[PDB]
Image (spheres, helix red, strand yellow):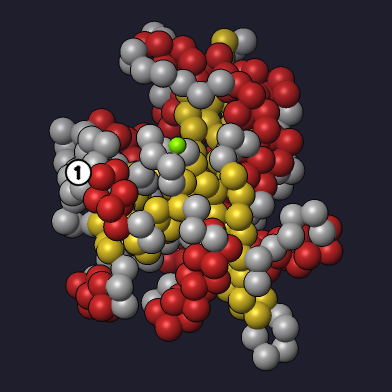
């Protein structure tokens, strides 16, 4: 069925399925639509013989240069996507709800890539975009397929961040704290302002754009302090670096960062260490440091994140496209 957002009871049922599913994704929670307030929300789900929700998909529709809409379910749907027959059923419900307004329904679940899975998907009619498309550009996948994920379940006895790493890394993580770096966290407006100054400063230094503060304010309004948390690193009165992490389902996700110019005393490591501590304190299975464009020492993002993730990057199946309008699809989507 399609979710009626004007019905509190139905919304709460939908939310409880999302929050409690081991496949839950924050970008699939209904709060996400509030963040992307410029997109149109359309949500659907499936029920079992008992009438209990067993699968869900939160879509967001965006405009294009054509008369068709772009339907996107960021990191969805919420279910075991390898159970393709069930996925087909969920997608059929999604397609019905789209009522022919979109040229495609794209979803990029965080499930490992494999030739076998890629083939099954293609056999069921879906168009997949992974090892077959450009690494970057506007033809590249929206989300990175390579992500540095720290699997905390490999260290059941771990009490603090340090217990997760070799001595060489313990030293790197200790350095900022030894040099006076202190980190406080929460989800207050003051902390948001703190994050925003470092976020935009970082943006300017790199000559890149940045999202407006209202984006993060909507995020702060949508998720409580047990879901959204801002970490701020300071040294003797000076603001050094910050980071935003979201806790949902089986993982804490490092989504945004900021750092002032000049001497930052390795504050970014301190921020990471505390986000990891939060994952440990809450018994979270995974700490997702985000994507990388290449597992190479020529990539500064890979370098940094490799400090905290020694395992190889997880490679996801990529974008799964249910083509609805083939002509427009070909015009707006290429490899
Ligand atoms: Mg248009």
Q: Position of residue 1 (x, y in %)?
A: 65, 72
| In the depicted structure, whether residue 315 falls above or below residue 174 | below
Ligand 1 located in image quadrant:
top left
Residue depicted at x 83% and y 58%: 8
In the image, residue 157 above or below residue 30: below
Q: Is residue 163 visible?
A: no
Q: Quadrant of residue 314?
A: bottom left
Residue at horizontal 46 percent and vertical 21 percent from the top: 210
Q: Nearer the viewer, residue 108 or 257?
A: 108
Q: State the residue at coordinates (27%, 62%).
A: 128
Measured as percent of width and height from the top left, residue 132 is found at 16, 56
Circle 1 is placed at which residue position? Answer: 135
Q: Examine the rendered structure and indicate whether residue 258 appears above or below residue 218.
A: above
Where 173 falls versus 213 (above or below)? below
Which residue occupies the foreground of this view, 151 or 81? Answer: 81
Residue 11 percent across, percent down from the top left? 76, 60
The residue located at (43%, 73%) in the rendering is: 81
Residue 27 makes an appearance in the image: yes
Q: Position of residue 218 (x, y in %)?
A: 68, 33
Q: Is 221 situated left or right of 235 in this image?
A: right
Query: Of 117 and 155, which appears nearest the observer?
Result: 117
């Amino acid at each position: 069925p399609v979710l009626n957002l004007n019905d509190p009871q139905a919304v709460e049922r939908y939310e409880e399925f999302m929050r409690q599913s081991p496949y839950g994704q924050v970008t699939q929670d209904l709060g996400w639509a509030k963040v992307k307030n410029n997109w149109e929300p359309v949500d659907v789900y499936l029920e079992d013989d008992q009438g209990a929700i067993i699968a869900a998909m939160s879509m967001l529709l965006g405009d294009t240069p054509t008369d068709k809409k772009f339907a996107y379910a960021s990191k969805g749907p919420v279910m075991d996507v390898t159970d393709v027959d069930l996925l087909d059923r969920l997608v059929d419900e999604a397609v019905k709800a789209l009522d022919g307004r979109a040229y495609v329904l794209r979803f990029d679940p965080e499930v490992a890539y494999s030739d076998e899975f890629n083939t099954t998907l293609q056999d069921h009619g879906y168009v997949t975009r992974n090892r077959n498309v450009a690494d970057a550009g506007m033809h590249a996948t929206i989300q990175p397929r390579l992500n540095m994920v720290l699997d905390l379940t490999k260290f059941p006895d771990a009490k603090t961040t340090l217990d997760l790493y070799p001595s060489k890394t313990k030293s790197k993580i200790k350095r900022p704290f030894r040099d006076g770096v202190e980190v406080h966290s929460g989800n207050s407006a003051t902390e948001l302002d703190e994050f925003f100054k470092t976020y935009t400063t970082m943006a300017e230094r790199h000559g890149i754009t940045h999202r407006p503060i209202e984006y993060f304010q909507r995020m702060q309004a949508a998720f409580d302090a047990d879901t959204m948390r801002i970490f701020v690193a300071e040294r003797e009165g000076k603001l050094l670096s910050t980071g935003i992490a979201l806790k949902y389902g089986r993982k804490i996700w490092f989504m945004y960062a900021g750092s002032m110019d000049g001497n930052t005393y390795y504050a970014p490591y301190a921020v990471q260490s505390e986000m990891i501590q939060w994952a440990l304190d809450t018994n979270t299975d995974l700490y997702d440091l985000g994507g990388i464009e290449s597992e190479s020492t020529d990539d500064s993002l890979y370098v940094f994140k490799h400090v905290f993730v020694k395992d190889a990057p997880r490679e996801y199946i990529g974008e799964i496209d249910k083509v609805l309008d083939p002509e427009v699809y070909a015009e707006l989507v290429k490899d």
